[PDB]
Length: 12
Length: 180
Image 1 (cartoon, chains in turn red, blue):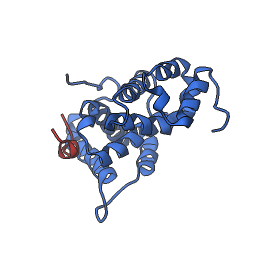
Image 2 (spheres, chains in turn blue, brown; image 1 turned 90 degrees about the vertical axis):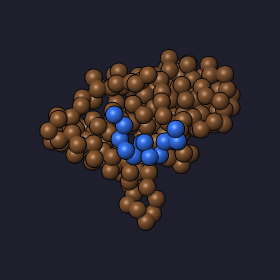
Image 3 (cartoon, rainbow over the protein chains, first blue to last red; image 1 turned 120 degrees about the vertical axis):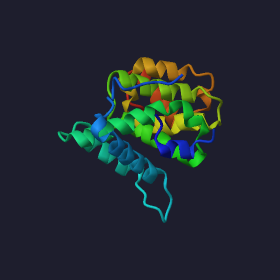
Image 4 (cartoon, one colour; image 1 turned 30 degrees about the vertical axis):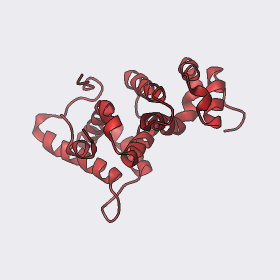
């Protein structure tokens, strides 16, 4: 359910 | 695995869930932005969240709920955040506790998330998330003496900043430290 901003900053 | 904090912060009505998500996303984009992109400070975001939390306007409460729910559900990803954004996140997370924007279950969860971060290796990014969050709500520690006992029992408590050691130890006794 993640907001795009968190997908963006996260290094997975 | 996937945490779900919707019992504290309910999901938005389907009718405007896209717009609520986009608004929440925008506030976070601004808290993490750098010039020349639009920014908001942690204090500005906290001021807004205080207004929204128990607003009589549904849209404002919905954006509050969306922001807090997502922030808390993000905890398992915090170790993946770059150091700059993680620090901002820590200040926001500690400020939420400081300003009483979470109570009961969510307050206990917030405290637990800070404690677990402080238990990570000394000098690690999550250790520093813990320290930054704790510094924001240190004036509340005397209200949580058992929590303070747990903090003091951390294996590298002796490496915490001096003032935090004081706040924690006096907090165990339900007291302010000798100077604040």
